[PDB]
Image: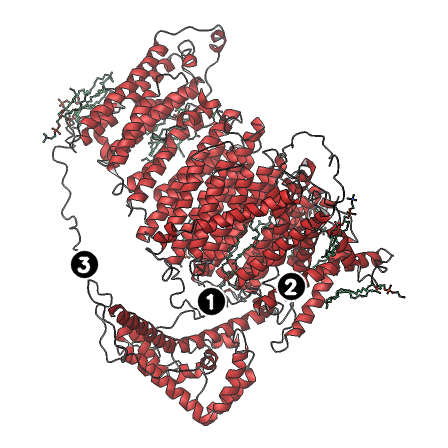
Amino acid sequence: MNPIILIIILMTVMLGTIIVMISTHWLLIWIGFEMNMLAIIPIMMKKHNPRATEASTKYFLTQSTASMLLMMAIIINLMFSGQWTVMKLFNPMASMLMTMALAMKLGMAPFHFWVPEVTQGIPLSSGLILLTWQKLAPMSVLYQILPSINLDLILTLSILSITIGGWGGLNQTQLRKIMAYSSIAHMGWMTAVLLYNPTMTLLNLIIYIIMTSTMFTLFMANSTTTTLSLSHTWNKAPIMTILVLITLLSMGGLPPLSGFMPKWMIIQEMTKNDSIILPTLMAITALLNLYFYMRLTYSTALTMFPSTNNMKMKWQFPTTKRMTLLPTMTVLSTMLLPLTPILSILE
Amino acid sequence: PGIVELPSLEDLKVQEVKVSSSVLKAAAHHYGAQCDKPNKEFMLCRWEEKDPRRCLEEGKLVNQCALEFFRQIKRHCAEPFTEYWTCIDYSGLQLFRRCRKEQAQFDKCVLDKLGWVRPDLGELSKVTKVKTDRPLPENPYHSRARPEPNPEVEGDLKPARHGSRLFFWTM
Amino acid sequence: VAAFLKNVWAKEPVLVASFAIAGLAVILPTLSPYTKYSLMINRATPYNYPVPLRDDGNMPDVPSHPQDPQGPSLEWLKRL
Amino acid sequence: SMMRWNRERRRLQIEDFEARIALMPLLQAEKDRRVLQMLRENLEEEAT
Amino acid sequence: MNLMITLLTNFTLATLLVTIAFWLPQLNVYSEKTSPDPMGSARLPFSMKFFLVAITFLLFDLEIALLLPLPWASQTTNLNTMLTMALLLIFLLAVSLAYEWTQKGLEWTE
Amino acid sequence: MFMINVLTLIIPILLAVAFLTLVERKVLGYMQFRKGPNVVGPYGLLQPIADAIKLFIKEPLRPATSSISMFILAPILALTLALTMWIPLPMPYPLINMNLGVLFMLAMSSLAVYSILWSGWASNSKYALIGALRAVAQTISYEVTLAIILLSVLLMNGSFTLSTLIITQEQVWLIFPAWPLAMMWFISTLAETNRAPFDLTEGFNVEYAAGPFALFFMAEYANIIMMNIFTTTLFLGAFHNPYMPELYTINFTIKSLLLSITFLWIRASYPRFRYDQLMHLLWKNFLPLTLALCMWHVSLPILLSSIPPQT
Amino acid sequence: MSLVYMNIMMAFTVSLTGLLMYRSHLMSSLLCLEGMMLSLFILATLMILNSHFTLASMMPIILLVFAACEAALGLSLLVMVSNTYGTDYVQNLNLLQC
Amino acid sequence: MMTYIVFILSIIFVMGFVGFSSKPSPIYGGLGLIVSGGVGCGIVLNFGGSFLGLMVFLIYLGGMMVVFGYTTAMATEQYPEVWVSNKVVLGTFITGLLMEFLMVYYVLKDKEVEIVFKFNGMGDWVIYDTGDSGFFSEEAMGIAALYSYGTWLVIVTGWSLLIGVVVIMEITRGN
Ligand SMILES: CCCCCCCCCCCCCCCCCC(=O)OC[C@H](COP(=O)([O-])OC[C@H](O)COP(=O)([O-])OC[C@H](COC(=O)CCCCCCCCCCCCCCCCC)OC(=O)CCCCCCCCCCCCCCCCC)OC(=O)CCCCCCCCCCCCCCCCC
Ligand SMILES: CCCCCCCCCCCCCCCCCC(=O)OC[C@H](COP(=O)([O-])OCC[N+](C)(C)C)OC(=O)CCCCCCCCCCCCCCCCC
Ligand SMILES: CCCCCCCCCCCCCCCCCC(=O)OC[C@H](COP(=O)(O)OCCN)OC(=O)CCCCCCCCCCCCCCCCC
Ligand SMILES: CCCCCCCCCCCCCCCCCC(=O)OC[C@H](COP(=O)(O)OCCN)OC(=O)CCCCCCCCCCCCCCCCC
Ligand SMILES: CCCCCCCCCCCCCCCCCC(=O)OC[C@H](COP(=O)(O)OCCN)OC(=O)CCCCCCCCCCCCCCCCC
Ligand SMILES: CCCCCCCCCCCCCCCCCC(=O)OC[C@H](COP(=O)(O)OCCN)OC(=O)CCCCCCCCCCCCCCCCC
């Protein structure tokens, strides 16, 4: 791809998300999602193999169906309110359809069935864009319509997201599918606290984006797409062996790392509202995520080490990859729990 | 809720201007010049009362002054006006520009026998002022009492008492 | 700037005519003395009823009749 | 030619619109009495 | 109503002429013909370029759909804004055509 | 009484299409230093009748259609869209007087490509389908410049109303302020109707019988006469006395006959384009000029203070 | 609720369930998706015309433009799939099972 | 019956969506969606939104379903059907369309008027011509205010169309 065309298309992705964030009119919300989808499709087809075309097709179909359901929600709101302000909705039918459409856009379960496939088919940088930047616009719309969101619906989608994103990561050796099921679990955590305190939603979204970008930046820096290929990193770049894995200890949510901060603040703000069963069971399923991701940590900085001979040739070459913000993102994703009351800046 | 209050059918009886649309359009500019004051009183009453039930007598004055206008045409300039609205009436879009000689003869007979100058281009679309003797409607929308707003913040901003108070963080 | 222009008017006169007409269409209405009259004609075209004002007692510019001297004029439009 | 004739057509449009404006109070009074007549007829038939 | 009556008349005349032009030569008992192309029997080859000209049509047709209310847009009171947005829409249609040019998109059906 | 008006529209359309075949064969005859038909009728007046009776009793080609439904609906849609393009035409008064008659004709002419596409798919041949796809791509390419030229001229009309376009041209023919739009419009109408030098289909619906081929042929000629009448009304607007409308009718009929004969005289004068040459002619020649003149006719009535009225 | 809007929503849901039940082709999926867009156009148009709400008259045109650009994107994706495999079958799009 | 023409066209619209949504083939699905677009355009035109219905015919059916049929003809390889003499090749077509229009009549049965006559739509349905608008269409002026009022909407729409051109030329090159 021509780098000018790449810059213009990435600015169009960013512009679509900014248009969703700043606009007060529902048609401009729908326009921002259309522009965001249209612009992100060539980022996925950047390498032109059949897997990226299949992934772009499945992503197009799911996001297109979600855009149509979003416009049907907007149209029902115009029926029952005669106006277009992006605020609460004035029909439970419009609220239900817009919550379903945004859950399809996030890949929350049971609309999760595209995220591991699409994340598998596309490269690591476009997978990073899809799992970090594309979450921002539907979480903004869910932030603005929360006087209308049905409680039982959003809690059902959140627990089904956390359970399916947990039980998806057992059978996986592909790193992109692991990050996709981690995405499904974390979006369930974010929408669990949405109707109680959406500042903790924004805290979980920011910490998740930092940890996800650290993991995808390390996967790009090591040229590893599978567990089996990630396990050759100790003989090639030994500082990458610890950074990937203590960032991955952050991502499951485990103290004293900063990925324990969002889940702890979510449990904290849901027990103010006299919900005790629900954060307990959601964090038990997060321990199931810890179970599988700790097995991956064992496989990379423990048992299955063995190397090949052509590592002897890779030893004579240093990295030229621009590991952009990787020490910054790695320090932010691990040592930020002593600065936990910084979360008031998101209020 | 409440009974909607409608005027009787005797409150709605007035003598009607039983002429066609080309007949109205042929005398339109002279009607706007000559019948200006009750028409403008009525349309001020109509955009202020926002209710056709509070405008019935001004509408009757409009209908009366229109009937006096057409009687005053009929007594003086019946044949040039008939010659003019017949030619206006032939057209599909009812053009003024197809009928300039009948317009000239109608304006000639009207300026001679009655002294009515046809208004220039720009005049009948002016916003005029109307002297009324009825009171201004103080609540034409019948809005009830507005909800009292939430109290604003006032006072200087003291620092947080012992900081964030988040479980053990002393600042 | 004159050798290139003759070279492109020799090679591609369709696109030279296109860029010249589009350039005139861009930078010409900013230079015309009649662009203000388009605005003045469009805002003098009475689609709505000129709703009159309640005469409070001090409005010496608002007329009482169309044929009164005060008020906006369209003699510039009849003359031009 | 189109300059002269479209200016003339705008003046003829303004003449037609002033004819409409002069006719509007009569038509508005008749429309008011029309809809009040129809609502009163429907009210009496609702009563019977 | 007059429109729909005229449409029904045109459709009925068209279907009547099609019915006559199919049934009138079938009254002939001519013969039962036995064993009734450049390629032999192979698959239809897909051509990427025909699809590209169809999509370029669709995108410029959507830009034309944006261009259509301009004779009504000329009547506005905000004429500087209207003229700027009209010239901007036709300029973005021209930028689409220039980008379609300079990436060899209009080639072998230019 | 309205049905009398509809039939006296649509049956003289079929008669004028019938004798356009005679006029085309005679004019192509005399321009090629020969004669057209003069034996069958007195100077060929019975040639369209003999041709129509021959085409409607000829043996059907007996196709194995890929679809029954599209094989039947492609001539029906071709004839219906050929006949509905005539009802808003102000000659001087339209049969159906509508506010958006220009836009109506543009929409019904955009619908006309489905007869080509369905006729090409409803045959078993792949070469017929390839020819139909090339014809559809040609037609959709030239509809772009149709729409943009038409919008640019309607910026002098004031509305989409066809009857207003006579009022627009009461002082000057509209070809005088818009002759480049007129000539690109004329070649674009020449390329809409698959007409030489743009008839590459004769260099898609050859699965049909002689009867249905006559139906596609007469839909094509109704489109040709219609587009010439529309171009006459659009650029060469006749004088309309509202008391004697037959003056306008004689005047636009003479002008539309001259423009149809100009189609006949262009097909007898030029070699055909190669397919990419007319794709080039659209996309790289007519379309930049069309966008530039569209900018020019947007911005010109604002700089001349000559914006036409909406009504 | 209102009468014709129930029909337009029912058409939307029928085309939804057509998109939500794949039979054979990706083109049929794009057809059901654009039928959903058509029903959205009709429903938005009937509301905005019924309400006499003037500035939303430009809304369904923008709906049509953005979603037909979306459909052009879908047709290009289908073409790249059909050039990969030969057909546009949805069962040829299953390499992301593993 | 003639009062209820918008409801009848909506019933035809729902039946056409049932027609192509059951998906016999993408080509017959495209044909059913063309017919459904025409009758839904008739629904729009029978409120008085004439520019929006002509936008349906000119843009939806005129460009987009053309490109859908054009793309569909370049896939899904054709095969013949029954072609026996004119009773079978056209008489079965006439009887099939007669059964389809008799189905359009047959879905309007006594179980339907229980929804119709209880919630009578006509009598007060199309309230578009309630009073006077003036010398304009409100629909046309609201569409025309895309240029004076809708500046941001024009910017984002034209930018998305330019980006659409760029995006199609990137993903179709295959390199
Ligand atoms: C006259 C003008 C000039 C005056 C100048 C006066 C000062 C002169 C010296 C200038 C420099 C001043 C430095 C800061 C002042 C002292 C702060 C302090 O000790 O706070 C006590 C703080 C609370 O104790 P306190 O008795 O209640 O308060 C005494 C004061 O009133 C404390 O005041 P406070 O109560 O207002 O403090 C507010 C609040 C007080 O704290 C709280 O409210 C409690 C919550 C604190 C966070 C707990 C998070 C637990 C979960 C995460 C654990 C992470 C893993 C641990 C570290 C692993 C290794 C990296 O602070 C925080 O929440 C901040 C977060 C903790 C950072 C503390 C400052 C670190 C600066 C240097 C960092 C170097 C790396 C050390 C390791 C990084 C972690 C500390 O102690 C702790 O939280 C325990 C950790 C130890 C604190 C850091 C000690 C700093 C010196 C380190 C030297 C050795 C470095 C070795 C190499 C690098 C490491 C391998
Ligand atoms: C509607 C009534 C009738 C109207 C007239 C039409 C009837 C006459 C028809 C004649 C026979 C045509 C038969 C078909 C021919 C098709 C081929 C053909 O003509 O191709 C078109 C040719 C194509 O060009 P070409 O192919 O010859 O050139 C080669 C092109 N390159 C280099 C790219 C390979 O020309 C055009 O496209 C021009 C169209 C008309 C443009 C009019 C411009 C007007 C002047 C503008 C201003 C100029 C000065 C610059 C600005 C100054 C500012 C101060
Ligand atoms: C409430 C919150 C509101 C919003 C606040 C801000 C949110 C920020 C969200 C960040 C989302 C990041 C999305 C991904 C980066 C975007 C730019 C991009 O495309 O980078 C990838 C790029 C591709 O280059 P390419 O040529 O494809 O290389 C492949 C090899 N040939 O280049 C590469 O591959 C180079 C390798 C390194 C890439 C590192 C990218 C890191 C980006 C994230 C930084 C951390 C997030 C910011 C801080 C927290 C914000 C919440
Ligand atoms: C500012 C106003 C708005 C301007 C933008 C809108 C214009 C309206 C028309 C839109 C045209 C869209 C397509 C333009 C593409 C330009 C690039 C191009 O075509 O380059 C190739 C061409 C050489 O042609 P070639 O590649 O060989 O094609 C085969 C046939 N020979 O190379 C060329 O032909 C060179 C083309 C560029 C140079 C033309 C210079 C004309 C200058 C006229 C005087 C100045 C007018 C004012 C405007 C500024 C122009 C710089
Ligand atoms: C808006 C205007 C539309 C106009 C449409 C029509 C255009 C054509 C106008 C007329 C052209 C010429 C008509 C005459 C043609 C020649 C007829 C003829 O001469 O037939 C002779 C033939 C044999 O006769 P026989 O008895 O053998 O003679 C031997 C003599 N010792 O005997 C026969 O063949 C038998 C008799 C046949 C007569 C045919 C007459 C012409 C039929 C035309 C049909 C349409 C008429 C117009 C309809 C619309 C207007 C009302
Ligand atoms: C396989 C099926 C059969 C295929 C062959 C036959 C069908 C295809 C060919 C014919 C297509 C017909 C298209 C008709 C609608 C065109 C747009 C239209 O109605 O424009 C006319 C007019 C708009 O002008 P305006 O002046 O604004 O309105 C009058 C108010 N003064 O608006 C009016 O005057 C409104 C009048 C009432 C509304 C009539 C709407 C049309 C009838 C319903 C749809 C019929 C066609 C369905 C199938 C379409 C193709 C699939």
Q: Is residue F68 visible?
A: yes
In this view, the mark in front (2 or 1): 2
What separation in Å lies between label 3 and label 1 (alpha carbons)?
40 Å
What separation in Å lies between label 2 and label 1 (alpha carbons)?
26 Å
Residue linked to disc 1: C42
Report which quarter residue A252 is drawn in. Answer: top left
x and y, in percent, of residue A317 in the image: 48, 13
x and y, in percent, of residue G89 in the image: 53, 29
Report the chain holding disc 1: C
Report which quarter residue F95 is drawn in. Answer: bottom right
Circle 2 sits in a helix, a strand or a loop, which is it? Answer: helix
> Considering only vertical position in the picture, is E33 above or below E20?
above
Residue linked to disc 2: F235
> Considering only vertical position in the picture, is B72 above or below H108?
below
Q: Is residue H60 left or right of residue B67?
A: right
Do discs 3 and 1 belong to a common subunit?
no
The C terminus of chain B lies in which quarter of the figure? top left
Q: Is residue E62 visible?
A: no
Report the chain holding disc 2: F
Disc 2 residue type (three-letter): Phe
- Residue A30 or H114: which is nearer the viewer? H114
x and y, in percent, of residue G4 in the image: 39, 52
Residue linked to disc 3: B146
- Is mark 3 in CB contact (under 8 Å) with mark 1? no
Decide: few, some or many residues near mark 3? Use Cα within 10 Å; few <14, some 14-19, many ≥20.
few
